[PDB]
Length: 87
Image (cartoon, rainbow, N blue to C red; front, top):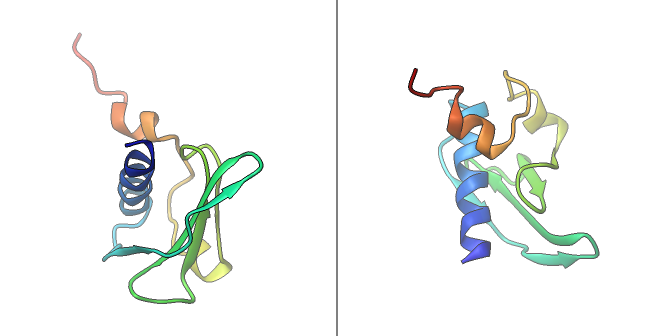
């Protein structure tokens, strides 16, 4: 389902920019004027909350969860391709 794909992209994206990622818990699923909005937290820490909508094009998180990121934001397709291809 479309909602299921968004959850998979967000979970995979979170661990890619966060190697210390342990688990992700969703608890919102609200419809925003732009489209959809999903919010949740990782490491069973309510303080570490994150919010995202359509695809991983737009991603927002708290300052405590922002410092966790060590690499710049990248699209789901960008990380999936990893610039790796046959040649």
